[PDB]
Structure formats: C-alpha cells, structure tokens
Amino acid sequence: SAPGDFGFDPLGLGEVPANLERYKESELIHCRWAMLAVPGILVPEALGYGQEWAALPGGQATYLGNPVPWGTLPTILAIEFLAIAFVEHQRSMEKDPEKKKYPGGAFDPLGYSKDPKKLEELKVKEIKNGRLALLAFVGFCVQQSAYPGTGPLENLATHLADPWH
Amino acid sequence: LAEDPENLRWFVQAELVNGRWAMLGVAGMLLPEVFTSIGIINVPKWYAAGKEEYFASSSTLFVIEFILSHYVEIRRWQDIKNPGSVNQDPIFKQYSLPAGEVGYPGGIFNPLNFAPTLEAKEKEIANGRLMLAFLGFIIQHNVTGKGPFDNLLQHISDPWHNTIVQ
Amino acid sequence: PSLVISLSTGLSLFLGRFVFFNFQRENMAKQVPEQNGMSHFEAGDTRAKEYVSLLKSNDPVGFNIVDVLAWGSIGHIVAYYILATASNGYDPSFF
Ligand SMILES: CCCCCCCCCCCCO[C@H]1O[C@H](CO)[C@@H](O[C@H]2O[C@H](CO)[C@@H](O)[C@H](O)[C@H]2O)[C@H](O)[C@H]1O
Image (tube, rainbow over all chains, first blue to last red; front, side):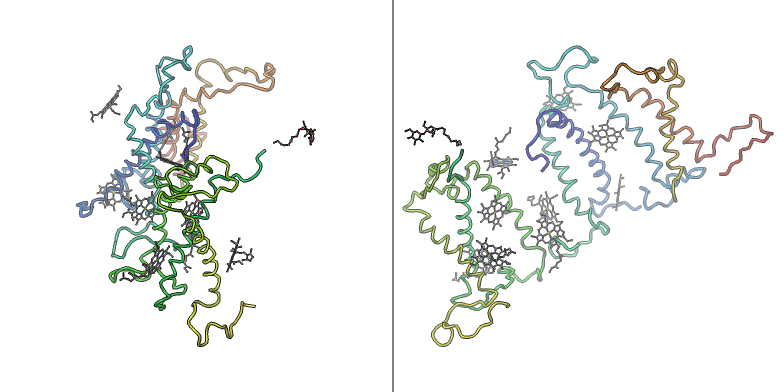
C-alpha cells in the first residue's frame, strides 16, 4: 500500500515514474535470471540425468594448486561486484533531453523538460507486467519462503494450512 | 462556527446495515423451531456439501471466503463519500437520485423517502430495529438455556433455575 | 573455518584505494590549503563538500585489492625474491 496514491516530483515522481521501476526492470530480469535458474524443476519428466555445481564436492576443475580460499562460493562471488560495475557506471551519467556537458540554462519552457530520459515511451504494458512480477516475488513466493525444506509430493486433500506454525 | 445536526451521510447508513444484517441474522435461527431438532451454538460448520472429501478441516472455510467480500465491501466506502452504486438503495435509498435533501448538507431531522413502487423502507424500518435488539435478546439468554415455549403443562410459568454464576 | 584473511584481504582492499596520489600530479596534500593558518572565514562555518568527485580511480586502482590480495596473500607472498640475504633475510614460508 506504499503506492496508496502519493507523490509529486523529485522524491515523488522523478525518482520513480520510470527510473526506479525502470531500474526495477532489473528486478524483473534479475527475477528472470532467478526464473531462468529455478525452472530446472518447472517441467516434470525431464531428462537431466546429473555437474551444475551441487552440495559442494570439489569445485570447477580442482585447480593445479590449492583452491583459492576454500569452496566454490568466493570464486564466482568476489569478481561479480566489480565486473558488472560496467552497467550502472553508464547508468549514472545520463540526463533526459540533450547531452553536452553542464551547459547554460535548461530548466523549463514548453515541451516541459522531458520524461524519465527513458520514459514509458508508450508501451504502458511493461509496468502493468512489472508490478505483477514484484507482487509475485513479494507475494505467495512465501509459499516457499517460510519452512521450505521438502519439494513437491502432492497426495490429495484440498489446499491451504493456516496457522499453525 | 458549526452549530448542531450535521453528519450528512454518516451512520444513518450504519443502522440500515445493522438491521438488514440483524434480519438476515435471525434468518440464522428460524429453521429449528417448527420442526425443532438441531440448534443452539452447533459450531455449525454451516450445512455441509457432499460425502466425498472433507473430514472436519479441508482448511479455513472463511478466511479464503472473506478476501472476496473485502473488495466488495470497501465499495460502500467506494460509495459513501462520493455516491455511486447504480441501484442506489442504502446511501440514501432508491427513487433514483433524490434525498439530496440530506446528501448536500443540512439534515436537522429529515425522515427521507424511496421506492418508485408504493411506500418505503419504513415498515421496513421497525423490522430493522426489532431484529437489531432481537439479537440482543437472542444472544442474551444463551449463558442460560436455548428453547422457546410449548403449552400449559409445566413450562410457561418458570419453576426452578440456577441464576448467573454468583 | 574462518576466512580471517578473507577480510584483511578485504580491508586493504580499500586503503590502497589509498596508495592514490602521493605520486600523481603535483605535491602532497593537494598542498595544505587551509589546515594551518585558517580559512576564510569560511565562517559559519565551513567548506567544502562536493557530491561530485567519487571517480578518478573507481576504475583504475580498484585493481589494488587483487594485488597483494592475489599472489601476495593466500599464494605465498613474493616467491621471486633473493636480493641480499646473509645478515640473514629469509623470510621463510610459514605457509
Ligand atoms: C461564529 C463565530 C463565533 C461566535 C462568537 C461571537 C458572537 C458575536 C458577538 C456579537 C458582536 C456584537 O453585537 C452587539 O450588537 C448588538 C446590536 O448591534 C447589541 O445588542 C443590543 O441592542 C439591540 C437593539 O434593539 C437589543 O434589541 C439587543 O437585545 C441588545 O443585546 C449588543 O451590543 C451585541 O449583541
């Protein structure tokens, strides 16, 4: 209920009208990454057989020389947060209408500044799908976020279970 | 500088919501009287559907139920501030759009109106109260007993009973 | 169990982000501006601050971590020595 009708410009709009939720287009695609990961289940009866890095038995290729720290965790980790500093560096050097330097004066006439640099540009349908993802990620994703140990083994009865807990 | 009787919309509504859910309330009773049989608290579990799958639980039979009710209840709030519900029969009652003799502020005592057909929720006023106060009675005498009247043998004269706790 | 050197690795991640500018332009201390002797006066007081100067080596000397922190930490610090050891030196791999 945070979007319970409120907001004006910089902290209100400005930060958000696309911007924060266009940066929440990342939320969806990171969730697209997370739901380009999890759908190992999704389709039952599949032919996975087995690698994929599970339960920590050794690592990538054992390494001709003792593993860096220990585990397969810091090897993929420590790098990530410096290589993907590619994107946002470029995301924090933008501006909306024209780009030059920090020139003379461009506050407002008619035409009215612009719209989130990258505005809706129309397709007022990505948002109508965005909040949906957010609600899904936030919502009944706690169908598996409270006591999530066992997988799927449905036996027949009905649904739900309440509290209890 | 505002003096007396104001409120406008307010809780003229509340009454007609209490009584209509006190009427449809005693409609909870009704059944176990002519052919008496099953009654009191019952913890009913309502009426129960077929004999296939259930067994005492099958989950909450009401919490799932009341999410539906919700966004079909705030819709009277989606009404009472700024009037809107085609039929238009509680907020001021029907007759279309009248009763603005209280919709635009300035009641004081205003009795009102409504129904192109004959009279009004007027002798469907009384029947509002009698039911809101009947519950009063209905869930007043539980705490001690659960049955109403027979004939002249040995009931309608009150013989011996236990009183309140102490 | 503990990556102990998980984090001392980590902290001189950042103060080599320190080894910085003793080298590169002009003098020390963007030369003492204001330090001793004492500001205009200034006076309310006073300056400066600038949300706009968190660049310059964001990109370059964000490598500094992986320096010592790679090959000079868990991988036995400079094996490529010899350079006058006889009053002693070595030095010798505790690892
Ligand atoms: C809504 C705002 C909050 C309300 C609080 C403020 C109340 C207003 C105060 C009244 C201001 C002065 O009003 C003043 O003028 C009256 C006539 O001009 C005078 O009134 C007098 O003269 C009349 C001449 O026939 C007599 O008939 C009256 O009985 C007598 O009271 C009083 O001196 C006083 O009533």
